[PDB]
Amino acid sequence: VKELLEAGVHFGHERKRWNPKFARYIYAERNGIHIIDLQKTMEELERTFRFIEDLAMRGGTILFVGTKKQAQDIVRMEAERAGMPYVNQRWLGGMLTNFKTISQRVHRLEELEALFASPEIEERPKKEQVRLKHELERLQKYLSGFRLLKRLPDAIFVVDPTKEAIAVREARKLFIPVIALADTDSDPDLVDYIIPGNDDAIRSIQLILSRAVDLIIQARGGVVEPSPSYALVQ
Amino acid sequence: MLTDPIADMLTRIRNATRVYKESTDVPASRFKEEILRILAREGFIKGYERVDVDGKPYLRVYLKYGPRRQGPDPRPEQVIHHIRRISKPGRRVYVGVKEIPRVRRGLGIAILSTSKGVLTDREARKLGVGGELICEVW
RNA sequence: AAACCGGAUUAGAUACCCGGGUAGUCCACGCCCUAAACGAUGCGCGCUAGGUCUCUGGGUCUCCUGGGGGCCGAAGCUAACGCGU
RNA sequence: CGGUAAUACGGAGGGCGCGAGCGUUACCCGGAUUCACUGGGCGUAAAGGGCGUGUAGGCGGCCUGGGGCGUCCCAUGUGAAAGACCACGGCUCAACCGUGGGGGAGCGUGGGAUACGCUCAGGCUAGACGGUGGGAGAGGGUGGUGGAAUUCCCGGAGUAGCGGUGAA
Ligand SMILES: [Mg+2]
Ligand SMILES: [Mg+2]
């Protein structure tokens, strides 16, 4: 189910904060706003999903990023709802590019997995039960979706690339294909497979980002429900 | 007044390609056309056609690029890397056939105007005539 | 208010501060022709994303479209600082 | 470089380089795209004229026709020898020399081309100028006039200081 499902509540977004490189994917300045030509949305979807498919059934790992305010959660849903890695709270200087080092944080996160369930089940110089169980605190918060990922992904999926630029940069540096949902905010030129959409409305992120995860599990057989995601959707 | 029309064209073209435009008008002249023909034939432009704008004769020039590109900065290679005026109203430049230049060991062109018409350098060399050395292009 | 005449200050003070004061500052006419006379950026024309503030025209007056003044800054340029319809 | 540990001075051992030579000085080109034609620059490095007006000059939109000056092409004459370059030769080699061959711009003559530049003749309206109608402006010149303030002068009322400074 696609087509008018998109016009559902998810077409055009921002106005007069545009990138004129995005002028190709626009329908009009109707009532002050940029409303985004959907025929070409759909157009780009086929090519993009086509890439996802092939990538997925060839057994690839996509890396999902959405640190954005109201995308935050509907990421770690569909990301985990497909066993793919995700970056949720904040992108870090050189997850990809400084990958080896940023990994020793995960290498050392699960050292503390294995100190919870431990012979030190309740022991070690008692003020070290915040000193270390608050190290695992931060480690937890950030590397929760990143922890799976043990070689660079074969792709990345991004919700707002002008928001998420520090990532996309690393991607392109590393020849890693950039998949993203992008609106009039953004610079198409450096998004390899674009979902000309709406970086913002939670429904729009949902419709799109879930289907893409359908396609992913569905390209290893075993489709499920209407997705464990409708947040407080409101 | 616009003092070197042919400079103009080369420049319009140089300019439009570095922002990867699909096309550029240039106000039309028979001579301009003759140069375009070469560009087209030598495979530098897709092609060109006459058109009007505000009802005055122009020449739409359809430009041509490489494929989308590797890593950070996906900008296509240029097909027209270099397009430069040689002869100019300030200083006219003429060559005998024995002294027509060879552009980038042949991987490039030099449009050049003769009394046997406008020609690439190999063209001119073959018909053993020289003339006004218009521009190089590689 | 240069100069200059005094009062302070100071190691001294041909200065800074204070009290006076002529040329000059003003006008007309005739000279002089200089400057950090600066955007330290000669003049004209064509081409090359945009955003926002502003002065002044026109339109079918959300806006669109000329001509000035600004800032941010595509592409690009620059030793850098910056420049950037 | 040298101020008491000098691979930099002087000497010595050793070493590098060239060799009937080796160094020095002078002068020329080079590198020096450091006068930049090839091949440079001028916001802050040196460099935009204080600004205009416009003389000579330089440069000149689109179309068509003539001419063929520039420009291009073919032929031809000229470009002595030496030298240069290539060959093969003579002095035992080489230097030196002989013989032969091949370059060659520039200019003259004859013939040809006409795209671009030039020129003559026609044509267009995209540059420029003009017309009608509207606008904003501390743009300039001349005359006139307004209020605030300072200074002096005259009158009133009024008493012992005012002024000025970091303090005086
Ligand atoms: Mg220089
Ligand atoms: Mg200077």
Image (cartoon, coloured by chain):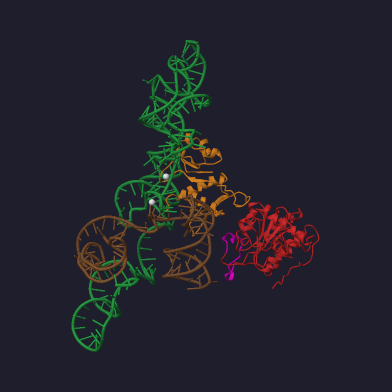
Chain colours: A red, B orange, C brown, D green
* Quadrant occupied by the C terminus of chain A: bottom right
Q: Quadrant of residue C39?
A: bottom left
Q: Quadrant of residue A216?
A: bottom right
B116 lies above or below C47: above
- Does residue B11 appear left or right of residue C22 in this picture? right
- Residue A44 place in picture, x, y as percent: 67, 59
Q: Is residue A166 magenta?
A: no
Is residue A164 visible in the rendered image? The answer is yes
C66 lies above or below D108: below
Displayed-image quarter of ligand 1: top left
Is residue B49 visible in the rendered image? The answer is no
Specify the segment rendered in magenta: A18-33
- Residue A119 place in picture, x, y as percent: 80, 60
Q: Residue furthest right?
A: A222
- Residue D13 place in picture, x, y as percent: 51, 24
Residue at 52% in and 46% down: B82
* Quadrant occupied by the N terminus of chain A: bottom right
- Does residue A203 appear left or right of residue B102 in this picture? right
Q: Quadrant of residue D151?
A: bottom left
